[PDB]
Image (cartoon, protein in one colour):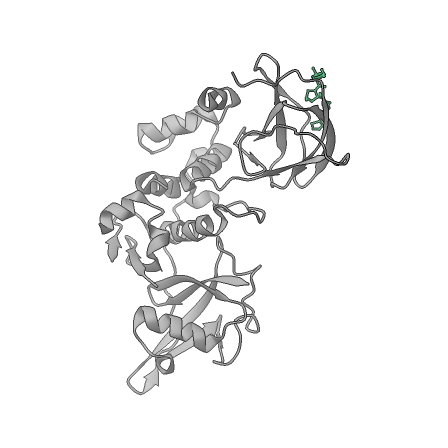
Length: 87
Length: 104
Length: 141
Ligand SMILES: Cc1ncsc1-c1ccc(CNC(=O)[C@@H]2C[C@@H](O)CN2C(=O)[C@@H](NC(=O)C2CC2)C(C)(C)C)cc1
C-alpha cells in the first residue's frame, strides 16, 4: 500500500495512506512522499490524520455515524489547520 | 471487523487498520512494508505489555469498538539495533496552549 | 419553488433520530416558509402524521447545523405500502473538518467575542455566518 509522511512543526512524523492524505487538496499540491508542516504541531496533525480515517470510513456508509470529537483546547488550532488544508 | 491503530515509536506514528482476527506477527509484516525492518527486529506493545506474535489483535484487547477510526488505539513499537532491543520510547505529542480567555 | 404540495393524501412517517443532536424537524409550508415542529431528543423516535408530497428537513435544534435524512437533505413522504409507515432516518453528516471545528468554536465562544479570536478575518466571517435554514433554502434553489 502507498503511504506518505506528514511531518509536524515539532518533528513528529505521521505515516498515513496516500489516498487518505489526498482528502486535502493542499496536501495533494504539496506532494504533486513527505510533507513538512511548519505551522502545524503534532497535537493538531495527529487529529487531522484521525479525521482522514474517520472520513474515509464513514463517507457513503449506512452504519450510524458518530460525532467527530474535538477537545476545546485544540479546536482553534485545528480550525486554522483545516482552513489551510481545505478539509 | 476492522480495528484502527496508531503504531508508535519515538517520533514515528503509523495510522493503519487491521482485522481483529489478524495477528501480532502480521502487524509486524505491515510495519515491515512501511519502515523496512523485519519482524524479528520489532517488538510490539500494548501499554507496557510485550505482544506475542501468534496472538490476534482482538485477544490482545484491540477491538473494533475501542480502536475506532476517530480515536485509534496505540500499539507501541521498539527496534533492535545490532544485538539487543532498545527500550520502548514514545515521544508525547505537543501540549495545547491555554484556552484563550474568550473560550472559558 | 421549494414548497410542499397540498395533496391531502395522508402519509404516516417515523422520524427516527439516529444522531447525538436534539433534532428540529422543519416542514416547508405551501408558500415555502419553514415551519418548525417539536424537537426530538437524541436516539428518540416519533410516529407522526404528514402527507404525500410534503417537504421536510432536519436541523440541530440548538445550533441549526445541517442533518441528513435517509442520507440526503430533503425528505418527502411517499405512499404507505401495506399500511406501513415510511421511515425517516435522521443522522449526522460527515462534516468537513472545517465545519466541525467551526461548530465547536461556536459552542465555546459567545458571538460578541468571535472578533477577539486570533484568526484571519475570513474565519471570523465563517464563524459569524452560522447555519440557518433560510440560507440553505436559497442554496437548494
Ligand atoms: C409530535 C412531533 N414531534 C416532532 S414532529 C411532530 C409532529 C407533531 C404534529 C404533527 C401533525 N401533522 C402535521 O402538522 C402535518 C405535518 C405536515 O405534513 C403538515 N401537516 C398538516 O397537518 C397540514 N395539513 C394538511 O396538509 C391537510 C390538508 C391535508 C397543516 C395543518 C399544517 C396545514 C406532525 C408531527
